[PDB]
Image (cartoon, rainbow, N blue to C red):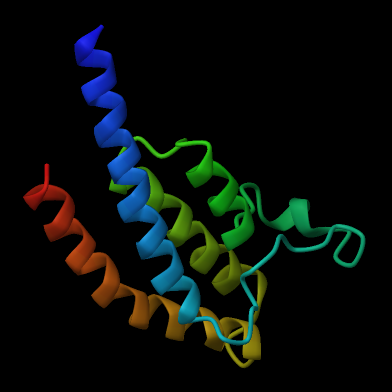
Amino acid sequence: SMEQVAMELRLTELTRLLRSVLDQLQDKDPARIFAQPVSLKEVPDYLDHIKHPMDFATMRKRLEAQGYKNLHEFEEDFDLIIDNCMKYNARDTVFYRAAVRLRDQGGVVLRQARREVDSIG
């Protein structure tokens, strides 16, 4: 149908918007602490602590498979990156501190993307 195509045009444009958002969020992590999954070879107990691991490479695979239906699902994944880190790592670690800074700095980007997604529909 003509409708399913118009739908697919918007999903593709949402994917296009979310890709830009993802790049902006990931620039707030210059140390690349959140770039890749936590290694289960190097942290073998990780899944006993964190039940839904997340990282920017994993979010990027989902994004390019147009696996995000709306901004809310995307934010959920971003929030996992942050909240997992803040549980697993203690307050006085470079890791916890990197998460706080990413949360704080990402807020501004996410605030405007919400306005943009409501605005462009």
